[PDB]
Length: 87
Length: 87
Image 1 (cartoon, rainbow over the protein chains, first blue to last red):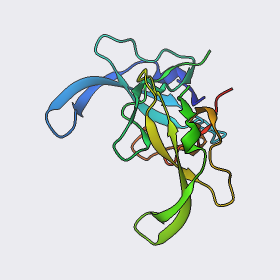
Image 2: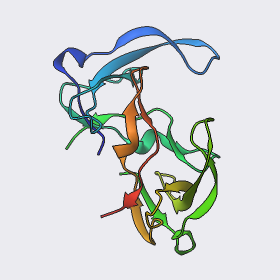
Image 3: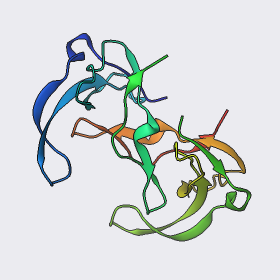
């Protein structure tokens, strides 16, 4: 399980000039999180916040492969890891 | 959990000219697997086989973030998903 802890100062997203894929500049809500990812310590990594979605509240987390996909290279590849609280 | 089923015809790796990262051609053992990844159906994806490691035997599987890492872009990123049997 790709655990992670959204610090208390990382419970709110912010609107920053985002870019889908070099097509157009989108102002989406971005957030942060701390994924140990097996690194023993928490790693403050960024995260996307759906429009209207509540920033990853303060709590434990576990990435979600719902964002992972199979590329034509025959190898899984995250397209936008969907973070979720750890149960 | 990134589930997956290593078909019965995908329980053995093969030695194919591999390339670490554009540095040198390595002949490692590669294998295959079927990760539904939430796609309802199984997706035959490729996989690497450590030298001396037994190809992903025939059984259920779940990728492993032990291969995932945090890039300097502030976003998790698989470096070489370590597949494992699903328990």
